[PDB]
Image: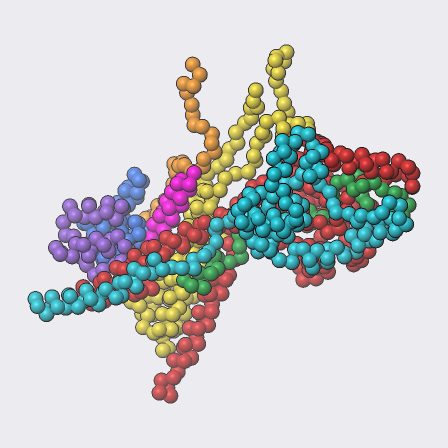
Chain colours: A red, B blue, C yellow, D purple, E orange, F cyan, G green
Amino acid sequence: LLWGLVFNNSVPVQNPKGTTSKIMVSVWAFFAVIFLASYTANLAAFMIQEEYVDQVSGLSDKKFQRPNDFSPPFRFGTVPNGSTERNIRNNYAEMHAYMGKFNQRGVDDALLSLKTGKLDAFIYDAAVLNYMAGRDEGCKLVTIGSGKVFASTGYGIAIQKDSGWKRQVDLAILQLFGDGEMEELEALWLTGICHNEKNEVMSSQLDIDNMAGVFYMLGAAMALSLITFISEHLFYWQ
Amino acid sequence: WVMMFVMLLIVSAVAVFVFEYVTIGKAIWLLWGLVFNNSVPVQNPKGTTSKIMVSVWAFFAVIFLASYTANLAAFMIQ
Amino acid sequence: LTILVKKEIPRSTLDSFMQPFQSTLWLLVGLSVHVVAVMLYLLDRFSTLSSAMWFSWGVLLNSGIGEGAPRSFSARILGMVWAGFAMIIVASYTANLAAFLVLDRPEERITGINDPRLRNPSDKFIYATVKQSSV
Amino acid sequence: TLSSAMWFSWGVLLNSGIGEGAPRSFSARILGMVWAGF
Amino acid sequence: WVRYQECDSRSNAPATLTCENMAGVFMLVAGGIVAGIFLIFIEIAYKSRA
Amino acid sequence: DIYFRRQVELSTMYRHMEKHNYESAAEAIQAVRDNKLHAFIWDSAVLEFEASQKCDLVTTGELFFRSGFGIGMRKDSPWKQQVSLSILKSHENGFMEDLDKTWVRYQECDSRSNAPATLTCENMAGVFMLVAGGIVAGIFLIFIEIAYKSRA
Amino acid sequence: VGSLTINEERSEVVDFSVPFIETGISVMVSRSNGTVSPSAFLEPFSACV
């Protein structure tokens, strides 16, 4: 009796005898109506504030290692002439040895290959990618983490070897940093639309097949119903 | 609220048909208790052939109140 | 001065007439209903037989159909978590129905003359004013 | 069916099925409809 | 002359009705009321047979 | 104090800054938690560590003066070509990523995203106390009812 | 002047100025669909409730 009304069910259940028994069930009903109305509330609070989690993180992941056990495996894109190739060829040889079949011919061609399912992930410089994250017509998912970069460096101005004109520009650039004029030069530079400025996620739950945990809470009881059936052989010895 | 009554009253024909092969005032008293989530002590109709339409109405009820609580919770925080 | 643009469509969730996730609003749960009726049948036979599905559907849909509880406790401990599962799926359906109607839509529009959609020009946006005017 | 009316009505409110009987008159039934709706 | 008419201030509040149509959820009972008599006829032909 | 004194548009702010300054980082860090000082200005590479250990304070976003801590040398020492190389080499083969993984981001409480959608259903006392009072008072009401049953 | 990174293989021949815009090697991931948690919210009601 006491399970059917706490979990909102009209199981056919005989009430207990007498009017004196009728009180405690009427307390339990007031515990039930408060209970489920709490739990539906908290769950509805929980499932419209939780954030999507970043299924690939870092270059040390098994996905970015040798892609053995993956229905069709990961395809990494890169441009094969520049600095990133010379950095990636001195730390992970087999990574670029696998990546050699997936070259791209341009930045926008990398975006067109990313939109058509032809590429799973793309590897390039940080500043150009942080610009192109902000100037897509949609503002869907962009970069791993927030701004986590692997080999932090800078841009610069190349110059003739040991010329005297280095030490002046070395002052003058710092004077620009001293004046805040880079943020005055921000109006052309990297601003945009949707730089994760909502952190919203709306999802049709075709991915509601994550309910396998409560299916595991089902079939475990489907085990225990056999187990107790086996311990219902104990009156044969008693 | 006006489609509810006119789709509610139509089961009297099958309630007559199951006794031909409990409907004067015991039909709508059953059909109100489960659409508004209540365990009113209500006799079910006779026969296993009557058991189908109530099992449709229960699926209309669970969809209904779960809709209306949803929309009200959308309405009262905007 | 101000900027004039065109409002969008955005829809309501009317087309989800009890089908928000009918891809994964599975009939697999109905097979679970049938096999748990078969399981209660097998638990009750070898310790009220053909009526087990008329029990179990009445557990799910909150409809009190005339029926008896299973006599063995081994079926009762399964029925406990079956009713708990029914409460779980109806509460999750309630929360995901509220989620469609509480969450708004993307495409935040342009804000003043300091927008890079408008400050830095392109082909994807067209701007115009009346000729020979104060603008 | 006279003294048990509150044991009906609390069972209408708190979703607790108590061994009782429906009112015989329809004039009480039409009040019970909107009581359950409330 | 100016503020005499409106439609609705576009504050983008989707929390409103337009529960105008209800067809796909009522069609299950509209199909149940028709198919139920046919299943009742098959059941009573079974009752008459055995 | 150099960055603020250099700017002219912020001069009034700098004139508001002269009467409350501190001498070390830990003094102001302890003084913020004692509510004597509502705000503090320092580097991000100290405050993001401080917001991961002393777990009552928060940063607030944007940056002003983007630079990096460098090795200070005497002018025209002969090591100026060696140490400018090896630093870049340590940025190449993954040494600094091990260094800050060992030292900087090793502890993290909770990215204060202000998500109240969580538990702390720890206590349940005021809702369970109705059944805890019902179980005690019910036997007394049953005794009064059976004294009525015995009487009439 | 332009887009030109800093590394060790170029610093041997060429001298460089002060670092100018922070950058590095990053990775752009696809624009995948939204996902809820892989379980129902069974977190710690089980501890006490």
Outermost residue toward the front?
A: F19
Going 23% across and 60% down the picture, which residue do you hit?
A: D18
Is residue E45 visible in the rendered image? The answer is no
Membership of B68 in magenta stretch: yes
Q: Nearer the viewer, residue E24 or A54?
A: A54
Figure quadrant of residue F140:
bottom left
Report whether residue G19 is seen.
Answer: yes
Percent position (x, y) of residue A52?
A: 57, 50
Q: Position of residue A22 (x, y in %)?
A: 22, 63
The N terminus of chain G lies in quadrant: top right
Left or right: where does residue C86 sit relative to residue A88?
left
Query: Which quarter of the picture shows residue F37?
Result: top right
Q: Residue at the location (32% across, 62% down)?
A: A4
Residue at 28 percent of width and 55 percent of height = D15
**Outermost top residue:** C132
Please provide percent x and percent y for residue C31: 44, 61
Magenta range is B58-78
Q: Is residue E48 above or below residue A182?
A: below
Q: Residue furthest left?
A: F152
Closer-to-camera residue (C52/E43): C52
Is A231 in front, or is A201?
A201
Q: Is residue C132 above or below residue F63?
A: above
Magenta stretch, overall SS = helix
Q: Residue furthest bottom?
A: A237
